[PDB]
Amino acid sequence: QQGITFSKNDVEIIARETLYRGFFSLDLYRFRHRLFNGGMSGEITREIFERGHAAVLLPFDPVRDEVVLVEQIRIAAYDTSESPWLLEMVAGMIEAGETVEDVARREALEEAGLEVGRTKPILSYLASPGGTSERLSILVGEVDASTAKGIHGLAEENEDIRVHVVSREQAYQWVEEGKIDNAASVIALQWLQLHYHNLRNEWTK
Amino acid sequence: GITFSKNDVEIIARETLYRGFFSLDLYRFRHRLFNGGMSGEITREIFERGHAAVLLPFDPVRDEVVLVEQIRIAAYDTSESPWLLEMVAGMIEAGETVEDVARREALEEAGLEVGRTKPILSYLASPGGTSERLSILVGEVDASTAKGIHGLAEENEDIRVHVVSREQAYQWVEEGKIDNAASVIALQWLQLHYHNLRNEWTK
Ligand SMILES: Nc1nc2c(ncn2[C@@H]2O[C@H](COP(=O)(O)OP(=O)(O)O)[C@@H](O)[C@H]2O)c(=O)[nH]1
Ligand SMILES: Nc1nc2c(ncn2[C@@H]2O[C@H](COP(=O)(O)OP(=O)(O)O)[C@@H](O)[C@H]2O)c(=O)[nH]1
Ligand SMILES: [Mg+2]
Ligand SMILES: [Mg+2]
Ligand SMILES: [Mg+2]
Ligand SMILES: [Mg+2]
Image (cartoon, rainbow over all chains, first blue to last red; front, side):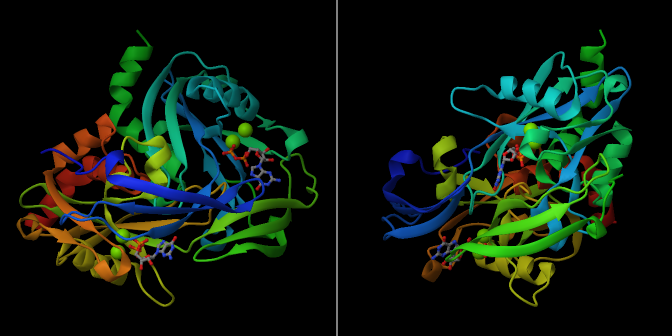
């Protein structure tokens, strides 16, 4: 097959407007775009949550077939989850000029006390593109899971994080059971379930 | 597993920062710390946009997947094109079931009737900044009936149906041609479960 039909040349962003600015922003995009049946749409407005973009690191120990998870409260999970404390991947915001890999390695140390060896890209995804611009770029990072323990996170920033080490099999079973249910961890761990055999061979050579 | 429960956090208040089609709320809360203490009062800005039902339309006889293409302007700044290849999906309104929304959107967005269904996974899109939860089902479809242009035109919805093989769709995930969370999650799940699913639905 061929894929998508239209490009950036087929949409005109007439205007953007920031409706709220605080730590994050809510922007109004005003645009018109080509229609599949020929013409151009009228003017359309969409509210878009703007919060920057993230680097995500799946810490995988290929010697032990183990993953390191970080636990912290995510209050937005409260209304639809039994607990707002989630088991997650290492992750942080990307600043201007920073690379995904530099952010991933720094956050692995800050959030889990982990040094990272080799890294490989997993996938880069849009979290929920009907309402937010956020893109997250996932790497897998080689770690020694026997070094992973304790409480981390930047305390001067109200970041309180607990490290957990589990087998890959257990982490994936938790995805299947819904005990791990945040997008970044689901995507990373499903990818690991599809790729771990080749990855362990590559990293223990 | 996790350490703390809802007994360990108090939401003191929520403040509406923005109310429009969607909302942005400030949650004010305190919570237990791993070191044994209580936090001070924490605030977080949270994007409130309701919750979604997502349908992976899978034809188990033909081993085919139905994708829908539509513009998502929020993708513009970080993507080659704002037109994305996606799963059928829609907002869940008050009192509706995930499955009822999935079936209605499959008809509106792809002209598809759905047979049997099975849950895939329900996930938080980005819980550091939004409450949004999306519940994915796989739905049995006849992909030969999936074609053409759909979407509710009276709602600025312009949608093109694409049919690909399962292996083709997954290759597109690997290559970055499909790169939205709902589709990546659904198609990775399908790559892990298709053998048993095809057997269940053809025998
Ligand atoms: N005015 C306005 N309407 C929106 C916005 N986002 C979604 N909608 C509405 O959602 C309907 C269909 O769009 P979509 O988001 O794909 O709905 P869904 O498929 O049920 O999730 C249309 O009627 C739009 O009016 C927005 O930012 N502004
Ligand atoms: N006060 C405040 N701080 C925020 C907000 N969003 C992010 N931060 C800060 O950004 C830092 C990293 O964000 P975090 O919550 O850890 O999300 P993550 O980077 O994706 O893991 C934290 O130290 C927070 O203090 C917010 O809405 N309000
Ligand atoms: Mg983080
Ligand atoms: Mg951090
Ligand atoms: Mg939709
Ligand atoms: Mg719809």
